[PDB]
Length: 99
Length: 99
Length: 6
Image (tube, rainbow over all chains, first blue to last red; front, side):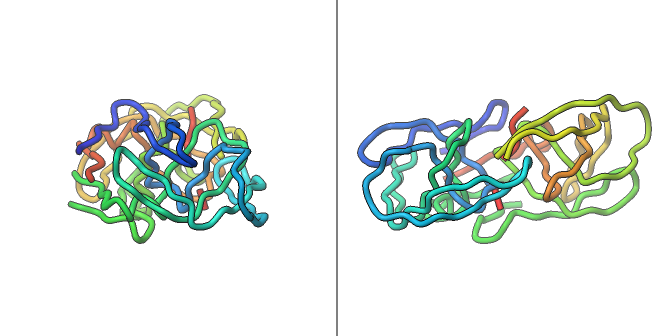
């Protein structure tokens, strides 16, 4: 599929069996989800962007299905206003920018 | 072009007669460039992201050449960690996400 | 305005 950029590129994902909305974000190194109650082991990390840094929980080898395309990798959990799918998972689903 | 996402999608832009590097950022509403002067009038604005809000200078109707494609629109100038081309200009150059 | 992670 093709997603235009007239509005934020919000799509349906599935993480822990549950459907959520997330932004396909080519400006994100990492995937940042607010899913504060996953089971599993995590480790503390700090990530940055325009306003500075925040604390997140790093979860590894988490399945994330993005618009029916399966991915599996690291998900960072922390307080964000929008769930964002970053390049660590976008590459797994074969996503490119085109113009 | 077609750009994959194994690396940050950095490209060269021309703005105000100068060459800069900037990230093609589908997760950005706006275009935000590190501190500099641009010609003309500006007004204060605040924008947010991952870490919170920052103050920027809002310049309107600024020509930007993005890997050889022309755009004219709002450019925000402020303490961003990396220069980013957001959807306001990505739409002008016809950029889509594809998978 | 929301603008995205390093």
